Each structure stands twice: as structure tokens, then as C-alpha cells.
Amino acid sequence: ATIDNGSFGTRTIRFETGRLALQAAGAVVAYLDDDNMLLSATTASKNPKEHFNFFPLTVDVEERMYAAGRIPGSFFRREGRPSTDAILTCRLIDRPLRPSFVDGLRNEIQIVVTILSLDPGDLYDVLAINAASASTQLGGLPFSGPIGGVRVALIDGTWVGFPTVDQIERAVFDMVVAGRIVEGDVAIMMVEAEATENVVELVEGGAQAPTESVVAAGLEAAKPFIAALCTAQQELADAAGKSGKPTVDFPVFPDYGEDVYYSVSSVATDELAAALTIGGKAERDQRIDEIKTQVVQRLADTYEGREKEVGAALRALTKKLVRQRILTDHFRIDGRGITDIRALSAEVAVVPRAHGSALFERGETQILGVTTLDMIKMAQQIDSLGPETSKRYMHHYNFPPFSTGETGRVGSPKRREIGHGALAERALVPVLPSVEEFPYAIRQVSEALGSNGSTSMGSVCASTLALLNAGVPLKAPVAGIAMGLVSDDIQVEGAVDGVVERRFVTLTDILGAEDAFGDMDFKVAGTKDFVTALQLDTKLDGIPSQVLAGALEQAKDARLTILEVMAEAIDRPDEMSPYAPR
Amino acid sequence: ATIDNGSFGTRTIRFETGRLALQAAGAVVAYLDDDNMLLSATTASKNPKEHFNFFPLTVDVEERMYAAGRIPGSFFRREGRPSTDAILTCRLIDRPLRPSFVDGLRNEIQIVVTILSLDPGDLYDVLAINAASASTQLGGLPFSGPIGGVRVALIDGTWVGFPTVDQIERAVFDMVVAGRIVEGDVAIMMVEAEATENVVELVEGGAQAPTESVVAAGLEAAKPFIAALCTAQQELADAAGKSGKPTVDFPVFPDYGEDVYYSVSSVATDELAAALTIGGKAERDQRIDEIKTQVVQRLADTYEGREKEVGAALRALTKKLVRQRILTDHFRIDGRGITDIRALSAEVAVVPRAHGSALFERGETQILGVTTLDMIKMAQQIDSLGPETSKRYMHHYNFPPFSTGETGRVGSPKRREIGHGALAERALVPVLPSVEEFPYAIRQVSEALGSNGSTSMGSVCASTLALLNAGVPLKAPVAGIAMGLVSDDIQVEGAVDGVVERRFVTLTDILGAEDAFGDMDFKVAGTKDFVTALQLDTKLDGIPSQVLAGALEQAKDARLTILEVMAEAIDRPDEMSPYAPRV
Amino acid sequence: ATIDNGSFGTRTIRFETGRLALQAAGAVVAYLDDDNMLLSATTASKNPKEHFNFFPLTVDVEERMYAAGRIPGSFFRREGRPSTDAILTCRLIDRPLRPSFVDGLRNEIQIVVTILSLDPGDLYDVLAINAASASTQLGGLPFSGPIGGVRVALIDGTWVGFPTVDQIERAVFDMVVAGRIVEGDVAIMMVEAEATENVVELVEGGAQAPTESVVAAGLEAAKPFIAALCTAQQELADAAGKSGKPTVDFPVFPDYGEDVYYSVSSVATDELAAALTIGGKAERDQRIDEIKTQVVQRLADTYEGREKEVGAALRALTKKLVRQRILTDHFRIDGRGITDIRALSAEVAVVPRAHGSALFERGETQILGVTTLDMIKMAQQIDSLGPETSKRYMHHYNFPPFSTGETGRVGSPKRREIGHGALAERALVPVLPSVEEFPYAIRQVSEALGSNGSTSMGSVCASTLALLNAGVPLKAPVAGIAMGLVSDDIQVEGAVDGVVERRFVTLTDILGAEDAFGDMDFKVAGTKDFVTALQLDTKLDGIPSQVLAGALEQAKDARLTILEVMAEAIDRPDEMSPYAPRVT
């Protein structure tokens, strides 16, 4: 509940309950220095639904303008659709909460958090995640927590926790870390990391560039704060310790109950690894399609009408066996090694009559990036509880239905599009030129012509290429890449008895299936000198520093390779387009 | 069809049909003085649906800008979403129409009324309800009407019917009354009453304040107009008399057909009143949960798969028996008396960094009110067929899903929120300070932290508290309260044979269950001197003046008690907030 | 792929594939003179749905502002809802594509076409339809094409193909023709025709007015271009010839499989034409309702639970027999002749307190038109990839649910409303007065009080009446009308054996049932001198010029009759309303 950062004063987080929203299943009011107020209320449905196929969890943040003491500027004088920052905060709170419930739950859960009072010099995302975690812990649901989040910024080589807006502009790197306590040592679920806007000028004058070692040190520094916050959530003045409640059982719907495993694993486990050794896309299935058909045919003698259960058992068995094959043989599905990158192609000036256009292809990902320019008056004007009003860089991300082959309805973007666009924009901001040198309004649009998985950083590279082609002077090109990590308790029979120990394997250019098979995923973006944007999320209970460092160096090597590949086409700013405005 | 108010000329309402919209089931064109034109068309579906659980009735008013001779100001030059006044009129017409059809109907009904020509000095809500009632009467549906609505304003001690905008600003009280004819004497279903903006200055100079006796006199004065309008609807030039049509039977889906009553009322009617005498919230059920389980278990021998029917029979039997217990023992479910008010709590300056903030709790209702101020330029700009353009007082009402414990989707407000917010704003307007003395833009927001039933006037009191805390000088604090009334034909055995006669009981602070058990509900809001906002709606066929007057005095006493309770915390305007703007 | 219009240079259309959007079922990039770029991608669902009752086909055009090199003017700086021109183009591409698939298909089909680069002096609708047709041909679906579209404008008596914006303002008539190849000669499915804004001044100085013969000549002139475009689609550098793909079978759900016909046609075919000879609206059914009830009752012995199949068989049999009766007896259902017009009524100044108001009734169609005026500042401001920015004439079309008797939800307009409103506005534009003479903002609204079928041109006439009543000086009143055509292979037994030959019958004032029974429908609008708006759509494989010409003259006669009927009420501009605003 208390944070001492050293010479920058102290911060206090307070958690109150029992006074507001008594009718809800759980409700917690969060105080930041008795100056910021917010309220989190979580309720659960009574009768679960059965037609749905996943866990129906909903999050709703509500920014209210009366906190800022200003009537809304809308024509009808009312706050309507959620803002982009609200959607980003909703995603940030939802991400470390879904992998914390009992699998297969069916009762609907809704978490509503509303801003009550906001200091103009502070932000509310971390307070929001803390209050939501405390409320859902007090709710009484099968929730495996509590979770704790901390925001830490690097200034003058020091990692100060919970910085304000007046302290972040003079920082070189910012962390938002969400983790829990397993046995006393923290276990991080997620982290979101961004470099500030003026990092280049700061590091030029003597400051330390945000390299990978600094990132690891920053991730290490945030653990005591998370531990203190979790302890406060557990045993504050009004916490779960003083408000013990009975736990009500919730019905759980599993994919396979008890028996389909004891059949399939004993009848359909010949090799289940040699069928995937063909290595040809046109001959991918080639053996195990017949295996699946024969299994679903000949097993239709004891379990009738339960094809979903047999499908779930088959897919789970295949996933486990390919995981074991990955761990032992170090042989990927596509035949690539653990440090291989798929085929690359970069084309410049593909769309005519445009200020800048480029096409970037990696494996199956294929992204077309277009950039335009106009008068400086065209900058976006926004107003919310946040301290941001102007936005000279407008990045839009489009994921049409025909990218993945399915059919749907083209229309309003989802939250995933907002998240990916925000991530790419925040990765590309720090290298932008100054307004005085280059006064213009830059609108970059990235359309997903073809997708297979992890296509955001392909869009990042394509946007860099298009910005360079348009003639915009960038300080240095910025690349991106995605990496995965599989950790498992493997058994070696060299001793008696079989010794079980944890082993880690890091993979490059993970597809959707690769992400499904793995347990940790992360994405690294940056330039030749330092990283800019980082996003990590997993469900492990600990990780040695050596393997994390090695994965970071592998990511750096892959990013350098991608940068060198992309620099072959165009490495210098191009001539201004005749249609561009002066 | 004709209204003679005395020295203020006469008004004429005309109902025409047979010329427009022949394809519809019913269609009526309404003329107001041959200067206002509107059209009402009602149609019914053919095959009723079965998955729905209530009566699917829809109302749609359509304000068209070409009546005002002005191109819409929208960017796309088209009238899109309905306006707030349209939603209010939709609610006003829908309210006295739902309790007029055969219960359990399943065929969808849609009533669409569109404005065709509007005089800038007149309103259209009462003409709308009249035209819709006439059209649905001509449709041929199982509709028990017709209904009639009248607008009556009090000026110079006289109740003039159908006032214009140039006559309402000099009034002290306004009535909209909707009623029908049962045996010759009118039977009012609904009434909506509001005090004007400049009532204080008018009553200060010699006019009569709108007290409860004046309200009763005004409600009494509107009956002849309703009778004349109903007679015109019945027997005008083009009415139901000259346009007789066959009545087509519509399938009716009941909760219990014929037999579940003869079982449950004979096997599960031991006391059904002693089980609710526990009086503890944690021990509320405590006897009748087991009764319900045993009834639904042991009766699963003749009716299988009809648990909905047995549930409906059980709930109806319990409602009837608790109604009888209320009538005879005068003992409420919670143990409170017929003139009791639940626990009260008022807190001021609860939300920091705000111009004004307050919290008000009554029983289970818990409302947080916040008020902010800004420049006078921030006044809301609107434009419609109505004569209103500016709105210095902006009241918003929020009902989040977690107030009542359920889960839903937070998003666009429904019509109930619009109605409650409009009611609270109209109740709080007349006491506002003048623009010259207090030039500011006032935006009040009321969020329902906790709800149990009838939480709008809790929001009214909370908004009054927040406005006082912000430093806004109000003429007098304004309170609100809700009351219920149960009337039933009780039998006394003191004579031979058993004498059946009507008895009335008035209850204070009605919950949802109390509203379900009763037959009449009303809500009274106002200050220590006079009332401001009134809303009444019921389904009775008559009421003596004495019981209505007594209920009004009981409401006045409860409102005075609430005002005295709330005045203990803060009774004077507070200091201006340092974050507030100076203008 | 190449268009030579004579002295106006040449145009080139290029179709590329295999480079973009590989994951889709089909994808084609379209080049217009290497200056306009667009992309069409079509994909199909895997498992078809069964609860739906029609073919689920969706079209989506996407105008992207980065083609014009301009940040969107929206508050959130993003292109949101589709524009009116986008909806019109969506309808224009969807219309000649639905009657080209195997009937009863259930797999969902989605066609998404996005603008990539647009020349400010060119349009994209015809390139859009061409690219979509090529993509759906390359997709591998059961698609009976390919289709070709051509835009042809008449300037100086010459029909130049693919005109630009700098060439259309000096034209007298514009055609968009979509047709295919059956045996070598083209077969037109659809055509959309409009007269330019300044046609009156042009034809006054010596140019030829766009009469019916000129329309027929223009429809004849566009065929070689369609043939060349279809040949290019078939055998270009990257076309279906070099990209042969297997055809995957798609399940087909029919209304009646094989047997219900052999029962109903043998047991319930006594006359099926005498039951409809009553001629009274209140006694319409009067015989065949009992026939339907007895058929559905006594046949419930072999097919149980298949009432939908028996209903489909009954309705199909009735349609075929009434078609034969129409062909042979020349006797319509309502008893009217082949050149009859239903009852007409026109009323002026019906809605009080309005600049102009009128009511027009024809048969069962009943339309109330209202027109208002305001300051010239009130002109609509729009911005898109198109070259249009201002719109002084704003026509709105409303179709409330209670017009046809059903119940629904009143709200956002559908695409049909947009299409009908755009058609009426484009028909009424060329006769509008000049801005300098009549500086005002004109907003006309047409509400469908009662509808039976083909009620758009009733709205056109009502809007003309209301504009005349408001005092707006029009050059000449404009009327509209709808006509149908039924062509069938009838057999005459005067020779041995029975000689089968094609016969055509043209009908006036077609209702919904008449449109269902027929095979060709068209709508003609215009003034006493020339036509303005034309819209034709059918599914024939050829038509002689003589019958088309005769149908055109019949339409002209009906339009003249309607004009003479409507001119009886008011024929001159009326006095300005006291509520109207004055600009002086």
C-alpha cells in the first residue's frame, strides 16, 4: 500500500470496501494519495449458458468527464462511445485475468470500473487493474490470484515506481508489470514496455540507451512493489482477511470427462510424429487425416454423438506429442531450425498516386502500407481525462476478413485492431522527426492482405518502409519480430530412477500452431541500437534469468537480420511526391 | 371535438379517416384548428410469436422537419436518431395503452404516428395520444377503450384547457390527464403534472401557490373535456359508429389454464401468511422455500413439464393472500407501519476534486450525485419542431447493471433512463436561480449505486444536496417520495349475508413487491410550500375524493419529514470550489 | 482489354492476379491506364447454413481516402459508414450477379472490392464490376459468366466508350451496360441510363434530343466493347485460361425434389385458370383457396411434414398456368388490357403550412410529396473520392412498414430506399432551374403512404407536382411509368408436328405478381420531348429489335397519357408561400 522510490517522495494506494455498491458481488474503492478515486464492481450471473463455447468474461472501463470538471464537448452533451485509451486499458486489464479462472467455466462474469476523480498529472490504468483484481478476489469466484500491477520508469539510471506525467517525459523507458505470488517469489504474467518520445536526445547527452540488459534489470526491479501490493490486497484495513466469505461451487463443462483419453491414447498413439515429417504444404496431412477418419469411425461403438469429445481428445494428444517432439528432437513442423526466418520480400512504390507505398512479405504474412501527408492543421483533436490533446502521427490497422480465408462482415474495428495499431504507433513514435523540421500531418494505414499469425510487426516494418519511401527523414529504421518459448518437465533415463527436470526451447517466427503448442510468447521491436516496444505475456511460475537473456539476444540477432534484409531495397529518404503538399 | 375555455376563444379537434393509408389496419388523421396535422397508423401481425414472454407492443413517433419549413442541420441533411422529446412522448402514449389489452396476447402490435404540420406556438403530445387511441380503436383489435387526453393549465385561478406556448409561460401548474368512460363518470388512468419555470415570482405577486387542494381541483376540472373527447372519438363524422367492422379473435396464451388453481389452492393454502412473519432479511424465506420445493416435487404426478404453470399459480396465490393480509391485519412484509420511512443517510462532499458531490441512501436505494460548472457558452444547443432551443440545466441519469445485482451490457441508455432524468430535471427546474445572478452551465449526473425500487426521487434529493454543496443558491430545497394505494372488495361478516365493500389502504416507501401487490402508485415531489412534479398511473374505475386527499396529505407529511432529515447535514450554500470557473 | 473510340485516344484495362491476396479463393487487381488501381477479392464459406431461405450473397465496396491523398475530415480521422455512392455501386454490382448462380445455393459468398488509387478525373463503378466478375470467375464457384460492363456517352452524335468527368458534362446521354456472351452475340442483363444536367441547352443549339431511337442505337453500340472485355477476361495474360482450377461441387437445396410435381400436376390441374376469372378483389380467391386446402389435406398420405414442398409446387404450377393464359388469351388477372392504366388521382396542396405539398395515387400506389426551401447556404457538403462536392437538390425516399401492411422496426433506411431516391433525383435533375435564376436549397421528401409495387415513379410524378406547386419554375413536367415483358416458347398445332416458336407480350402497370410472372422489366421516365432516366434488367439470351422498339413506343404513349392526366390539376407555377424565405 506504500511505495518508497527514494528521493522522489512516497506514494500510497488505499483499498476500501463495505461502503459503496453493497448489492454487487464485489466492490472496491481505490484511493491514489487521497487525490485519485475510482470504483470497481464485479458481479456474476446465476444460471450459466450452454450454447457459448468459451468463457464469457467482459470488462468495462468508464471514463467520466465530471472528474475533470468539464462539460463534454459532444453535440448532445453526453459521453457516448468509448475512447481509444479506454479500449487499450480494457485490453490491458483483460489480458492477465482470463488465464486465471477454472477452465471451462460457463457463468457470465462482468467487471465494471468507473473513474470517480482524476488528478490531471496522473494516470489510472495500474490503479484500475489493482482495483479490479481486488474486487474479483473479494467476489468469491473461482479466481486464482490476486494480481498486482506496477508502473516503473527509468530516469537517471534509476527505476522509480509510479511516475507522474511531469516525470515521464524525462524518462528513457517505461514498464507496466503484472504478476502474482506463488511461493514468495513473484511470478510475472504480463509486461508492457515503451520508450519515451525524446529518448534519442536524452541518451545522446550521456544517458544510457535502453538495451536488453537494462530491460532485464527493469523487469527485475519491479518485483518488490508487486509483492507489497499483493500483501496489501490480502491484508489491508478492509481486505479478504477481515471479510471471509464462503466459496460457492460453479459448474464446469470439460471437453473430455474421463474415458476418451484412456481409449485414444491406447489405440491411436502409434507414432503421431512421423505423420508430420512429410514437410510439404500440399502433403501436410497425408497420413493423419486417414488416422482421424478411422479413429472417428471405428470408435463409434461405445460413444455415440460425442464427436466433439473425441476431436478434443485427438487434438490434445497431438499437441502433447508434438510438444514432446519439439522438446527432444528440436525439429519444427515446417522443418526450419530454432533460429530460422521464413522467406522475405520487400517492394517499394507499389501503389501509384500516393505519397508513399510499400509491400512487405514474410512467410505467409503480406502487408501493404500506405502513407499520406497534408497540412499541419489536420492534426487529430481529442479530449478525455488523459493529458493528451494532439496526435501528429495517425496509424490505422485493417484486418479484412479475406486475409485468413473466412467470410464475415466488414465494418467497425474490434479491440484487437485497436491494440495492434496502438502498439505499432507507439513503437514507431520515438524515431519520428521534429515538428519544426518536418511540419506535416502523417497518416499511415496498414492493411492485412494476408495473415498467418503475428502480423503486427510485419506491419511495423512495412510502415517504416513506406515512411522512408515518402521522403520522411527518420533517424533510423525500426524493425520487429516475434519469438516463442516452450518450457517443460522432461525426463532423462540416464539415472535411476528417471530424473525429471525443466527444459526451455526458444523458437523464432512462431505461427498460430506454434503459439498454441508453446507456453510463453513475446514480441521485440526496435532499431539497431536499442529496443522501443516490448510486450510479454505467459502463464509460468518462474523463469531463470539466463534463458530469458538468451531469448533476448536471439531476438536481437533476428531483428538485426531483418533490418539488414530490408535495408537492401531502399536505405535513404526518397524524393518528395509531386502530389505532396508544401 | 370542441373545447370552450371561456374568454380565451375555442379549440376544435377533428378526426378524419378513409382517405389516407388504406392498406393499414387502422389510420386516422388529426386536425388541430385546421392548422396542425398529424397521422396515426396502426397495424397488427398475422402469426403471433411464442418465444417471447410478454405483449410485444411498439410505439413510434416521427417528428419531420419539413413541418417547420427548415432543412435539417445534420451533416448528411437527414433526421436520424429520435430526440429526447420524441422518447418522452413515446413513453407518454405507451403508458396508458399497455394496461388496456387482453392479458397474454402474443400478436405484435405497432403504432406509428408521424407529424405532418406543426404550428410554432402549439404542442403535439395530446393530439398524438388522441389520434393513436382513435386509430387503435378503429383497428379492430381486442382494445378496451377509447382513451382521451387533455392538457389543462392554471392561469389566474382558472383551469384553461389546451393552452398554447404563449399562454403556458404565465401559468402556475400544468396537467396532462388521460382517462376513459366506464359508466358515464370518467376513470383516469394517468396524469402528468408540472409547475412552470416562473411560478415563484407569479405566486409572490398575489397568485395562489399550487398546493394539494389546487391539484385535486385541477384533476377534477379535466373530466368534462375527457368525456367530450371520448364522445367525439365514438361518434364524429368519420368514427367507429359509421365504420363498423367485425372483430377477429386473437389467440391468448395464459399462465395457468383451469386446473392448477383447483389443486394448489386446495393443497398448499395452510397459512401462506405466517411464513412471511419472520421479519428478518437473512431469514426471509425460511419456511416457504421448503413449501415451494415440496409443492413442485409432490405435484409432479399429474402435470409433468409444466413447472411454469405451477410457478405462476404459486406466485399468484401468494400475491392474493399477502394482499388480503395487508388489507386486514395492516401488517407490511418488512414489519413497518403504513406511515413509516426506511433508514436515511445523507453525506456531503464524498467525491473529491469536484464542484459538488453528495451521497443519499434510503433503505436499499443509494445514489451518488455529482454536479459541475463551466462557462455559459457550454449551454446545450438543440433544434426540433418544439419551441425549445437552449437548456442551461443538464440532468443525466445512469442505471448501471450492477445496481440490482444482474449482469448485462453497459451502453446506450434505455427509455426508462430518459423518462426518469426528464422527470427529475423538470422537478428541479422551478427553484433554479436566475441566469443574470448565476451565469453558468450546470450539468448534474445521478448514478444508481444501489437500487431496490422507485429510486428516481432519491436521485432528486441527492441532486438537490449536490447543488447546494456546489454553492448554487437555490430558493428552497426540494424533496421527493413515492406512495402506493391498494383498493379491494373486502367482505365483513358482521351482517347476513357477508357484506362486500371497497376498502383503501395507503402505503409509504413501496418496494418492487409492494408495487406488484398494489393497484395504484403515485410519486410526489416538491418543497415545503408547494409541489412541483406529479406522476400518477393506475387501473381503477373510480376513487373517492376523501381517500385521494388523505393520501396527498400523507405524502406531504412524508416529504416534510424527508426535508427535515436532509436539512440536518447542510442547510446553506457552501463555498465555491477552487477548481470552479469564475465568469 | 483495349478500347478505341476514334479521335479521343484509346483506353486500356489490365487484369492481373497471382501477386496479391493469395489466401483468398479469388483475387484480381484491375488497372485503368496504369493510373487507376483497385483490388477485388472473393471468398466462399465452407459449411453452408440451413436456417436461411435465400442465397446469402454480400457485396462490399471500400472507398479509401488515401487514394485521393487527403486525411479524412471526420472528427476521429477515420472512414466509417459507407457513402451513398458506395451503396449505389454496391447495388449496381449486386444486381447482375444474383441471377447467375445455381438456384438454391446455401454457401455464403462475400465479394470485397477496395479502391487503391483513383484518378481525380475518372470513375470506378465499371472497373469495379469488371474486377468483381473476373474474381468470381477465377474463384471456382458455380458461376455462369463472365459478365462485362461498359460506360458509353453520347457526344456530338457519337457514342464514345469510357468517358471521363471532363467529357461527360458535354454529353446528352450516358449508358452503363452489363452483358455476357451466349453464342457469340451479346446478351445484356442490365443497363442504367441517365441524361446529363445541361442537356436542354445542348440540344437547343443543334444537338439531337435523346429520343427512343437514339436510346436503341446506344444500346446497340455497346455490344462490341462488352465482347472485347469478356474475351480479355477469358484470355488475358493472367486469366482463367492460364489458371485452370478444379470445380468443387456445392450442395443444392431445392424447393421440390422430383415427385410432388408428378402428383400435383396430375391431380390438381383441372383448369387453374377459371378460378382467377372472378375479377373481383373481394372475390379474388373464391375457388382456389378451397383447392389449396383440399390439396394440402388429401395429399397428406404419402408426404407428411413437407408442406413447404407442396406449397412451392402449387405456386410454381399456378405461375406457369397463368403465364400460359397470359400468352394465349391475352387476359390479365385484374381484367385490364395490355395497354391499360389503373385509376389515377392527383391532389395539390394537401399538407398545410408547407412550401409545397401534393398527393398522387395510381391504382393502389399512394405517395405524398412535400417540398421545402431555405437559404442557399444550406446546400449539402460532402467529400469522397468522387468529383462531387455540392448538392442543391436533396431527394429523400421513405418506405414506412405500414405501407404494405406488415409490421417491422422504423429506423435506418435500407439500400433499396437509397437506390429509389437516387433514381428519382437523377430523373428530376435535368429539368431543374438555374442557380442564378432560382437561388435556393430544395429538399424534396417522398413518403410511401401506400404501396403495391413499382412505386418509385409514382413518387417521381408526385415530386414534380409538389415542385410545381411550391412555385419552382420547371422547364417541363416529368412523368414516369413501368412496363413488363413476357417471352415464351409457345407451341402452335397448325402444322405437323407442333411448331414451337418464341412470342413476346408487353404489359403495362405491372404489379408484384405481374413482375413475378414475367421475365423482363423496365422503367421509363421523361418529359414530352425525350426520356431522362432508364433502368433495364432481365435474364434473357437475346431479343429482336422490333419488340423492344414497340415496347418503347408503348411506354412513350403511357407516359404521355400520364402527363396529360396530371396536367389537368395544375399546369403552371403557383404563388410563393408566405412562409417561404426570400433571398432579396
Image (cartoon, coloured by chain):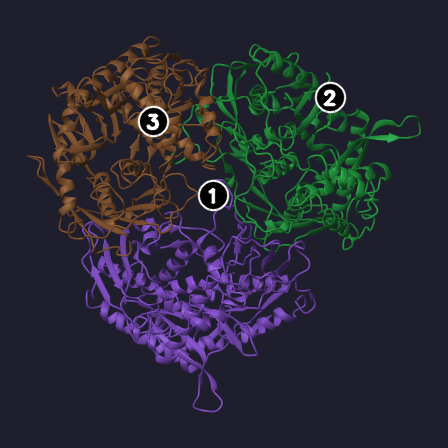
Chain colours: A brown, B purple, C green
Q: Quadrant of residue C510?
A: top right
State whether discs 1 and 2 lie on one chain: no
Q: Secondary structure at mark 2?
A: helix
Mark 1 nearby-residue class (10 Å; few <14, some 14–19, many ≥20): few
Tell me whether the residue at label 3 lies in contact with that at label 1, contact meaning CB atoms closer than 8 angstroms: no
Residue situated furthest left in the rendering: A7
**Residue B173 shows in the view:** no
Tell me whether the residue at label 3 lies in contact with that at label 2, contact meaning CB atoms closer than 8 angstroms: no
Numbered mark located on residue A557 in the image:
none
Q: Between residues B398 and A415, which one lies in front from this camera angle?
A: A415
Q: Secondary structure at mark 1?
A: loop
Kind of residue sitting beneath label 3: Ala
Numbered mark located on residue B74 in the image:
1
**Residue B476 shows in the view:** yes
Q: Position of residue B448 (x, y in %)?
A: 31, 56
Q: Quadrant of residue A317?
A: top left
Q: Quadrant of residue B200?
A: bottom left
Mark 2 nearby-residue class (10 Å; few <14, some 14–19, many ≥20): few
Say which residue label 3 marks. Answer: A516
Which subunit holds the residue at mark 2? C
Q: Position of residue C416 (x, y in %)?
A: 60, 39
Q: Is residue B315 above or below residue A135?
A: below
Q: Can you tell which of label 1 and label 2 is closer to the viewer?
A: 2
Distance between the Cα atoms at labels 1 and 2?
Answer: 44 Å
Q: Secondary structure at mark 3?
A: helix
Mark 3 nearby-residue class (10 Å; few <14, some 14–19, many ≥20): few
Which subunit holds the residue at mark 3? A
Q: Is residue C251 above or below residue A240?
A: above
